[PDB]
Image 1 (tube, rainbow, N blue to C red):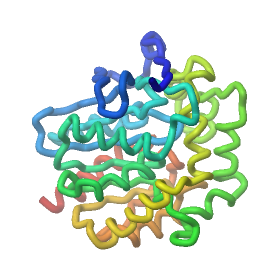
Image 2 (cartoon, rainbow, N blue to C red):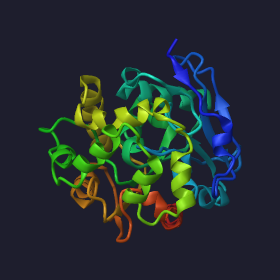
Image 3 (cartoon, rainbow, N blue to C red):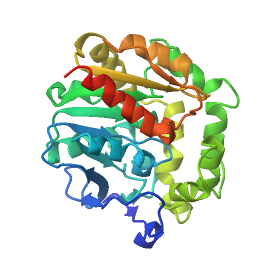
Image 4 (cartoon, helix red, strand yellow):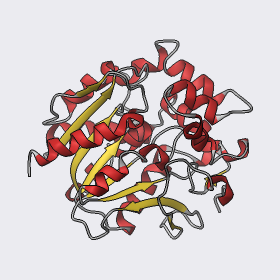
Length: 310
């Protein structure tokens, strides 16, 4: 129905630091015949579930340093790949990808797997989407680990969540240009530019899902959706503000990647004010947008903060 293609398995034979077994679902309501991949690590009967959402243009691979820390703490860790990325299937038309297409997949996943006592772990698009999930079924959500992310609201309600789109020229403007313009988009090259500490092998793990441009439509549409917010996106994200400010009563841990030109402190401090009970943020000076690249530390510190309240 949705025309999609699947990455050949051999593309992932040689991954670095990614020893996690695949789990796939292909009978999700609303996503007929599309196979989604997800990691399910740690004790499957655990009381606490860490739901780790990735962003643009990555995959669950991004969480490889944090997963073991969480699993070791006794928790179950779920890390899905959105349709268009990782080992999940990839719709070939950019038009198939929408804010709701991705948000509905998440609600579908959550129900099918019946996740409860969720500690939401988000960054980038994983956060633009993820922060809009709790208001749909608050009982399943208990904690939040937020890294460089915000809400896709309109410019008037929260100017901080729109300002970055236009300035600086080497921030969001550069990012989007790098992603949507090349006819021969090399993800490994893009990653090394935006996450300067990745090794060559790590960089290649980010290119692994895309043999050629035909597998990259999802990659291409995410940046455009930051630039062009549809009405459902705006309404849903606006209504999420209310949730975090008045309704949220869980534990929160915030980490900021200080070198991020996109969603740094000028986006994060404002986000901190909107989240009821958000504590002082953990500022990681050497980290850029991909906070997860300095993840072991974020994971360990968050667990310590949360334990310091049990």
